[PDB]
Image (cartoon, rainbow over all chains, first blue to last red; front, side):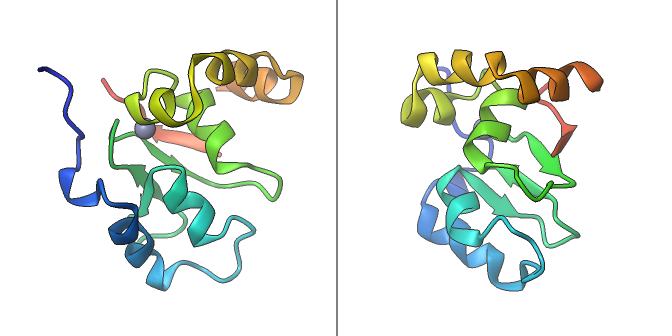
Length: 105
Length: 8
Ligand SMILES: [Zn+2]
């Protein structure tokens, strides 16, 4: 072995969805999408963490896609690799808008 | 979105 989810308690997406109970209705990204992308709500602002890699994302923009942001900033994630595949992770990083996003900070 | 935490 060697790999193990950073947050085993949130490996079940059904449990991840539950954390979005207090998710701001305000945000364009909906609980279903975020939970399916492997994220669970931190309960603070719009901060979410991935159960698998433990990476945290915040300050979501209107046109952000949970899977893309996941693959873009946390490309080594085992969950992203498992669900979306390596080709997708590579392609995401080549999209102009995302490439610039990653170069910015 | 911005990654406030990236795995070490
Ligand atoms: Zn992840």
